[PDB]
Image (tube, coloured by chain):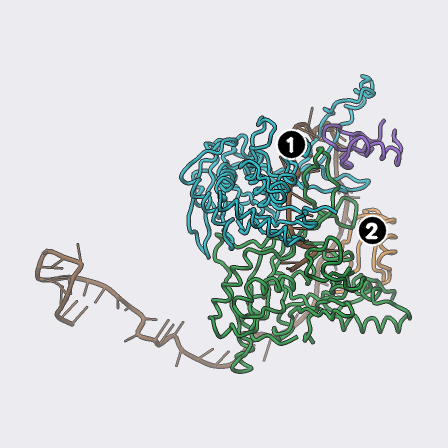
Chain colours: A green, B cyan, C purple, D orange, E brown
Amino acid sequence: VTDPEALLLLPRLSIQNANAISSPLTWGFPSPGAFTGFVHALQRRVGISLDIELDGVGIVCHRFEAQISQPAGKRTKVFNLTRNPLNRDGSTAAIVEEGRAHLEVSLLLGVHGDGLDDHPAQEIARQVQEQAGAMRLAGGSILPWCNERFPAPNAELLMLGGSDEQRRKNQRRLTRRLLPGFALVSREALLQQHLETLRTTLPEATTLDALLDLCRINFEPPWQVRDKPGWLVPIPAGYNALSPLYLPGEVRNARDRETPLRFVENLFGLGEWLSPHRVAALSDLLWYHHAEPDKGLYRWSTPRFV
Amino acid sequence: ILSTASVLAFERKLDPSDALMSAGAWAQRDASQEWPAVTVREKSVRGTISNRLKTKDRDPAKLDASIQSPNLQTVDVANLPSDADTLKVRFTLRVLGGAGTPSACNDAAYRDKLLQTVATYVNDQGFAELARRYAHNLANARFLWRNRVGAEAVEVRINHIRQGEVARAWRFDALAIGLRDFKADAELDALAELIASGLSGSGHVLLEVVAFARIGDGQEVFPSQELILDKGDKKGQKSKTLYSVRDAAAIHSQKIGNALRTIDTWYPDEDGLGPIAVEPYGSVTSQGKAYRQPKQKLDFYTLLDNWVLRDEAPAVEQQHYVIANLIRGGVFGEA
Amino acid sequence: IEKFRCSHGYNEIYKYSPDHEAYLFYCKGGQGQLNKLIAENGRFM
Amino acid sequence: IEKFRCSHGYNEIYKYSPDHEAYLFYCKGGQGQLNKLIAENGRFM
RNA sequence: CUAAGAAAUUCACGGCGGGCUUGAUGUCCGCGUCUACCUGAUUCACUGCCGUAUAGGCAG
């Protein structure tokens, strides 16, 4: 969509029990839809008051730790669960496996609007930080950095630079700040061209199979592993329609009766974990919302990446 | 007619973090920011059979053949160092606020009726009985679950954290504040007004809770234990796994939350237990028995329906319990 | 010599290992998981 | 030029190194470990 | 307005029994490391005198 007028940096945010179950096919880091919905919840809660439009999100993930455990004698992993309460008779309830993970991410969220000129930059930065302190990011509480050495503050970098050199200079200053992490971007063109080459190899190939080929460490005979460009992962890239769009007060047991509902299903794209100084433009690497509601296809990606 | 909403969901207010445990010596507790962490390590246990036998394993030949084959595990154990007698358990707690507003509600008529009922309660009697009990469960170190039962002296330090620095510091003797009497004190009531202003306001109030306990040199501490199904197949594995965030033993946040919610002294069965955790159909996991059964009119759901739908306001203790469930959270709703 | 031993109060299934002469921890569960494991693997080694 | 050399009475496997022109001590073992290492790495460098 | 919203794994435990790793062995020939520099930037905030003084001055 539209380009950001400024680039706010929420600092290293600790999330204690995020949803490690991203999707029915992927586990690990939470879905980027969690971060885009979080930024839209931030806009819904302070962006209408500071007259700004917080839009887009850059995911950095300084550290990650899934609450998993590899069982004895297996190559796979399982999830450490919680003990839910008993039922009304004292019987143990049926265990529903939820993944939990401890994250330390920082969010490069793009901000544009008329509120940039009305308030100081540090003022709106402190406002959205004090709002995000009372929120949750993927089902996990945001730990607010109390009584450590020093709180990591904000810096709203203005994307409009007086030069190209000043723009690259404070961009390099920001990239040094979010440097111990690993930026997550949407790489769907590489998945599409990998589909084309794999279809050239053997026809009627799905890009589900191209995704699966880009995930696995496949071996080749002369033995040599297939090289992979970068840290290629599968991500859930939004939802696809399974149902016609129902009326607000038509579907039974919705969340609300003023919003149209539609039964949907995940869409598994591809993402790439790269170091944040590779991109040379932090105006990119932001995850936006692309609905196109008449067709379905509610999805998120990083447009203007390459 | 004002029927019950089909999707009800309240977010968890009183959100704690994972209680990191570290260890050092008492009477240098004020320099306890570089105390080394209590680490979870492995040890082999070997036991004889001590369970009850099922009356077909009571043949003395079968018993003597059984006790010649012991049963070997490798448990996780967390001990203090041999030159450190104090366990420092340190977690943070966000008191969020907006305690009555549901995160999801279907019927807007039911939503406004619930907001009117909650505001009727708050304007009538604010969060002053509830936050007093939450300040008690922060004050006595009940979140020290088994690390409290044999301690010589437990001291809890609670620091209100403003934008980057401490705004107000408390200090309690957690053994004097009992585990069953919600009495009155000046500092406890100051903490109660702080948690009340947290739960009533729009923004969050953040507290840092530190608890020290003199256990003894090298004694065993009890971090949270992990619930893992599928322990493994056809090998030897661990029977007991302890929680540890980053090579540092820890209590789960939901165990700290269950300790903080242990305020319910109003369940109709006698208080041989004392306070229990605030839950709909209030069910103690260790007891295995669910008090506040729906057979009596004293669980959460029927009290909420009588309070909101047909305006049958219950006793002040029971509506304390109902608003304590609303602070607790939950996912409610029928088909 | 029994292949599985349920520790009854503690909800643990111990499977006999032949290398060392002892039982080792197999999985959690009670009498139902014990009987199901007996049906799958057969008792008495 | 052979990649492995078993010293037969002394139960030592010597693997050829190319930097210095000599064999160096690889591991212990006899003809079976030598044949297994030949099957894994291939002889004749 | 975040595969949203919720959650106590836990009580007990004896891993010890015992033991010979050994014989043998040539690392070794050969070699050019040179070239050229401001440690000084106030870089020694010193010693003492008058004064009751630490207040304030003075001398070199």
- Residue at 88% x, 36% y is C40
Quarter of the rendering containing residue A197 = bottom right
Chain letter of the residue beneath label 1 in the structure image: B
Chain letter of the residue beneath label 2 in the structure image: D
Q: Is residue B103 above or below residue B324?
A: below
Q: Is residue C32 above or below residue B249?
A: above
Q: How far, Cα to Cα, is label 2 from label 1?
A: 78 Å
Q: Secondary structure at mark 1?
A: loop
Q: Is residue D39 left or right of residue B156?
A: right
Q: Position of residue A161 (x, y in %)?
A: 53, 79
Camera-side residue: E53 or A95?
A: A95
Camera-side residue: D20 or E25?
A: D20
Mark 1 closeness class: few <14, some 14–19, many ≥20 residues within 10 Å: many
Give the number of the disc on residue A120.
none
For residue B212, say whether it is visible. Answer: no
Among all residues in the image, which is located at the extreme bottom? A163
Q: Amino acid at mark 1?
A: Tyr
Q: Which residue is mark 2?
A: D7
- Residue at 45% x, 43% y is B191
Quadrant in which the N terminus of chain A appears: bottom right
Q: Is residue A55 left or right of residue B197?
A: right
Quarter of the rendering containing residue A81 = top right
Q: Is residue C31 above or below residue B279?
A: above
For residue D18, say whether it is visible. Answer: yes
Q: Which residue is mark 1?
A: B291
Q: Position of residue B259 (x, y in %)?
A: 57, 39
Q: Secondary structure at mark 2?
A: strand
Callout in the foreground (2, 1): 1
